[PDB]
Image (cartoon, rainbow over all chains, first blue to last red; front, side, top):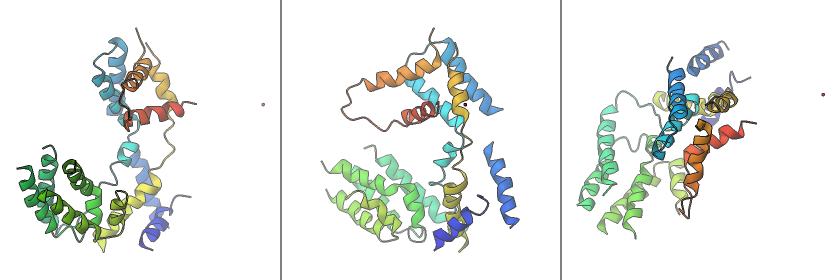
Length: 180
Length: 77
């Protein structure tokens, strides 16, 4: 019922003066930079018919992100997360652990992982906040490692992890269901 | 709990009031790219075309295409 009670709160001012603070907030969320970021792409693309196709690809990503500054913000929101002020110190070293494995993704390769993943096995915020881990997508990161391996001892430590990923909640388990 | 409630409010507020139909800009955009040599809109188009002609044998997600397709799809007693 918890997500549904949130969904009941979500359809509050969709159609309480508490609803009034929300409606004021959405207008504020909406929006000189958006003009010029738009314009300079149009400046470039007009005058100087553009080769190096990498550029052109780069331009319209900024063009669309600037026009859609809502959908840009859409994709950011499932990744974003609020932690309490207490357990911030575990999260710092977590991302420092995870940043090592994102780094080691592009690869002794075996060794530093197990130290890295074993750190993630033991963090306080792996239990208390499973929704943060799925927002990290780090299961897939770990998965892609054993994708990369499986064409040896390195594997099982990922597999010890990915099991241990499944236990902590059910929508956290959903993610792994897609890779059966 | 508080941090948990602010968490699920975020995904709840994401799934409710950010799905806005305010996005009517597409008509103004595709007008705006259709200005002066080759126009930018043709540059955008040809970008995707020459991408597609590469024999990848499996196309990728290419969210660039996924965006400007939808712009151009929204481009239309």
